[PDB]
Amino acid sequence: FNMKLAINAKTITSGLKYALATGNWGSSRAGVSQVLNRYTYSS
Amino acid sequence: PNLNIVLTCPECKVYPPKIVERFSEGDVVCALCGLVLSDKLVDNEVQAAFAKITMLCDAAELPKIVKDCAKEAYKLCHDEKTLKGKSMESIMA
Amino acid sequence: DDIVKNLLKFVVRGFYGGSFVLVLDAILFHSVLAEDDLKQLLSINKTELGPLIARLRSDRLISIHKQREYPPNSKSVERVYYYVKYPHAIDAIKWKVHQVVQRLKDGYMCPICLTKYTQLEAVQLLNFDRTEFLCSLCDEPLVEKQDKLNRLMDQIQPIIDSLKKIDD
Amino acid sequence: MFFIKDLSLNITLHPSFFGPRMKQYLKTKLLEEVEGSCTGKFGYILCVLDYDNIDIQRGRILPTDGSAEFNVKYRAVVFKPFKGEVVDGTVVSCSQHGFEVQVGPMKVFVTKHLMPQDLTFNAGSNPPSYQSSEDVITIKSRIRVKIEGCISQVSSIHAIGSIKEDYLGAI
Ligand SMILES: [Zn+2]
Image (cartoon, rainbow over all chains, first blue to last red; front, top):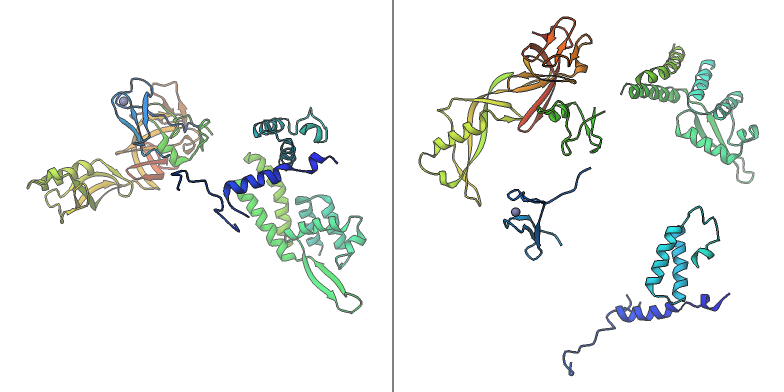
């Protein structure tokens, strides 16, 4: 038993990173994340 | 058996092909006589090993390039005679 | 049934090894057996008897009737009846020997192209400039047992004579 | 076998040919293409009979290219070789596999395996000849050949025969 092997960080890390990249919460949800519009400060 | 296609200008024939290719017109033309050559140019053990290896490099936070170099390495060793053992822990490390 | 037994022994000599021949002879010694009787009779196991039984099932060599002994003591009785069927064996042996003779009774190829040509292709492949058969795409040269099959056929001929004797 | 048959053919005039004399042009293209050509179905086309009575039918124009198409019904003599047929021929080319028999427009090949045992190849002769126990097969020599098989291809024909059997061999 060694803690580093027991806990796998990319589970959480790459999980969230993935989700926000694709914006699919599951599909059970999609398009939740969207790249910001910098067209104009109003936009 | 043969099957290799080469492009040659029947009117020039002077050299082997020296040509340019036009992607927009999707055609390929001899640069000399300006003739069109072509048209309509179109646009079990292992997997287990790489799985646990993947886990290890992951926990180690090594960048994918390192992970993949090690993967490549391990494939070359694989089942070879001279290794003759080491139980799969030594090889992964 | 001596002639049929001799034909079966010849088939055992031709087809498979000696253990199958011995099992057939053991079935010949005892009139009828049910699914467990070869195991009591033989030192081989039931799982391995099963591979041999599957091999017999692959061919027409013998026949199986599937019968239950009805009397209601526990689950009753699974008794299998293995009885040789002579007509199916005769038909299969004749088909095999005739097919074997047909195979024994039964050309141009290019080394680099690995293609294959025939006599009609010979008329096409002939060139007037040289004297040779030339390949189609690669224009490569063209290049290209029975007596031994006949000797093995001498073994087949004794079996055919035995079949004729069994017929008449 | 030299036969005669009524044959149909479709022809295409480039527009520039449409002058009143065009029918002549039709008969011209007909003769040029048809005579001397081969067709896998009817054999080698030899000569066109009944030149004057050729039926023009009615010329249809097709879609783009504007070229007039026609259907010509004519009567002509053609040669169709057949399997199990006995023919006579004069050798032209000689190979170790056999000598190539010229029968009419058609070049028939005979395999050495289709030749009798006594018949042997000779490369020590100029040209190479087949010297049997009696007959000697050379280029200008005449040989009676029964055709064993025929291969018919669209636009061409080629075939095989054997002098092995009786009433065959050198003429
Ligand atoms: Zn060019």
